[PDB]
Image (tube, coloured by chain):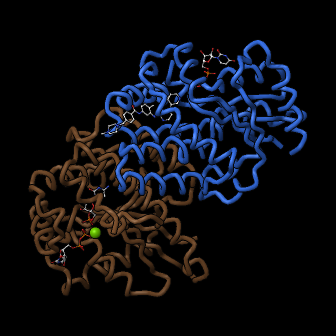
Chain colours: A brown, B blue
Amino acid sequence: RIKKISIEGNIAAGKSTFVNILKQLSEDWEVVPEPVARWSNVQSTNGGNVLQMMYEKPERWSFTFQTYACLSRIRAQLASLNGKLKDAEKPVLFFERSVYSDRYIFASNLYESECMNETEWTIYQDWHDWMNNQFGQSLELDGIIYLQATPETCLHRIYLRGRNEEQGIPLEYLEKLHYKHESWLLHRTLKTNFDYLQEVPILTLDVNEDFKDKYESLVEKVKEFLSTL
Amino acid sequence: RIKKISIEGNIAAGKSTFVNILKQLSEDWEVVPEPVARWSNTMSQKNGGNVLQMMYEKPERWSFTFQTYACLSRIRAQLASLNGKLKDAEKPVLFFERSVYSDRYIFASNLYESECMNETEWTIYQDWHDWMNNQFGQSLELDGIIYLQATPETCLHRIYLRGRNEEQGIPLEYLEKLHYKHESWLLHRTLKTNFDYLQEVPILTLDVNEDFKDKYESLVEKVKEFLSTL
Ligand SMILES: Cc1ccc(NC(=O)c2ccc(CN3CCN(C)CC3)cc2)cc1Nc1nccc(-c2cccnc2)n1
Ligand SMILES: O=c1ccn([C@@H]2O[C@H](COP(=O)(O)OP(=O)(O)O)[C@@H](O)[C@H]2O)c(=O)[nH]1
Ligand SMILES: O=c1ccn([C@@H]2O[C@H](COP(=O)(O)OP(=O)(O)O)[C@@H](O)[C@H]2O)c(=O)[nH]1
Ligand SMILES: Nc1ccn([C@H]2C[C@H](O)[C@@H](COP(=O)(O)O)O2)c(=O)n1
Ligand SMILES: [Mg+2]
């Protein structure tokens, strides 16, 4: 089977930018991008933007978004496992975010932020729990690449990307998710219902400096982490 | 193997009355109660109550949240029943109080048409339903459907006979809109579904208009009949 690697990080940290660098560095190295486009134009597998609806009235749409987001990821991630990489010697599938960061970082943060009531949040937890243990050892990650950046850098990279929905985001929101990231992957004190995660290796890279051209060091680091996997 | 039959019908038609009768008749006969119907009385049941109270309170906000949890519940209950006591029983039949297809094609459909679910809610629901079902519940495919036919008028009476105070509000107009949905689907079979096999699933239509609580003999004799013909 394929080594499943997850690239984690805050909003605008540099996930797609870095994951594209690695994507290009090898055949049998493939990527599973977060389906942000499906959330942008809700068309069935013209249509509304559920990423916008959530940022505009989070108290109204957080649960509906958080649900479609996770489901769209699950779908995509599975769909890739079946991809050409199946018939390819020594393969590596690089996932842009994971089912673990949807719940324990974003959805968790919204419930805490009072944008999901106890009921909304319980339903989501039971759904995520039940739904995830229906694959077994299928979507289990082999390793995690944490792309570390200040919530300050993120706010600036949000303002470079220039996606309308998120131009309203305050430092405080990024600051909240940052802390959640640090507790999950750096200090590793964020307990999850996924007991295997406890023994999963994490490579933490400080992607604060504009690595777009100065990325050789970052790539040397991934290649070493992957050998040890 | 276990034969899957679903009991379909409008509100207060007599589904829960019939699934109880059938349950008592055979050791080989097991029944799967509607999650909604239960909640119309342990976190899976605690959430149920909460969401159903909000559902009545403001259907414009909780239609998606409800039709979602109520359907995941159904899949979870039915997948659990398949691995139950019937597994090693000589000639087993599993009766389902309403199906995963009625949730979507009658109720969830009606709520999108009521404007209680917007287009974006509706797109996501249809997509969530298409996926959940094609992955997890591919076994929960039906062997047959027993339609419990009753005039919207009959149901309106049996809603009072029931007495659930929230239910006492339900207009005849609402029951008439749901009636025509059932009739188009199961009786005329003009209702188009995303599930291709439902074009050739056998349907026994029973006229539950007369009180069957005490004269259920013939009704069961026609079921016994239908079961052999699968
Ligand atoms: C369980 C429930 C409670 C209330 C409602 N609907 C309403 O209560 C309601 C109220 C007003 C309108 C019309 N009006 C349109 C315009 N907008 C702005 C307001 C509403 C429509 C529906 C649906 C449901 N949904 C539902 N879904 C599945 C099953 C059942 C159900 C209920 C009882 C017994 N058996 C099954 N019920
Ligand atoms: O070294 C870097 C990495 C990222 N970015 C910019 O930061 C924004 C967000 O990047 P990305 O989509 O990769 O972030 P993600 O949210 O996927 O982590 C984009 O405008 C990038 O060009 C940048 O200027 N320099
Ligand atoms: O032959 C019958 C069947 C049902 N009922 C009454 O109909 C009401 C609702 O029945 P049920 O719960 O079976 O309906 P469902 O909503 O499940 O279709 C209850 O008060 C029953 O006692 C009745 O009077 N006679
Ligand atoms: N469960 C999730 C997943 C993603 N997002 C948002 C954050 C971004 O605005 C976008 C995904 O792109 P990014 O790579 O910038 O995080 O969706 C969210 O709020 N909740
Ligand atoms: Mg992105």
At horizontal 30% and vertical 51% (from top left) the residue drawn is A184
Q: Is residue A62 above or below residue B78?
A: below
The picture quadrant for ligand 1 comes to top left
Q: Residue A183's spot in the image, x, y percent? A: 25, 49
Q: Nearer the viewer, residue A82 or B180?
A: B180
Would residue A203 be visible to someone looking at this image? Answer: no
At horizontal 28% and vertical 71% (from top left) the residue drawn is A15
Image-based side of B123 in relation to B180, left or right: left
Q: Residue B98's spot in the image, x, y percent? A: 63, 36
Image-based side of A136 in relation to A121, left or right: right
Q: Nearer the viewer, residue A70 or A22?
A: A70
At horizontal 83% and vertical 43% (from top left) the residue drawn is B1
Q: Is residue A15 above or below residue A152?
A: below
Q: Residue A39's spot in the image, x, y percent? A: 33, 63
Q: Is residue A10 above or below residue A33?
A: above
Q: Nearer the viewer, residue B204 or B177?
A: B177
Disc count in the image? 0
Would residue A87 be visible to someone looking at this image? Answer: yes
At horizontal 78% and vertical 47% (from top left) the residue drawn is B202
Image-based side of B114 in relation to B181, left or right: left
Q: Nearer the viewer, residue A219 or A137?
A: A137
Image quarter (top left, top right, bottom left or bottom right) of the C terminus of chain B: top right
Q: Residue B109's spot in the image, x, y percent? A: 48, 47
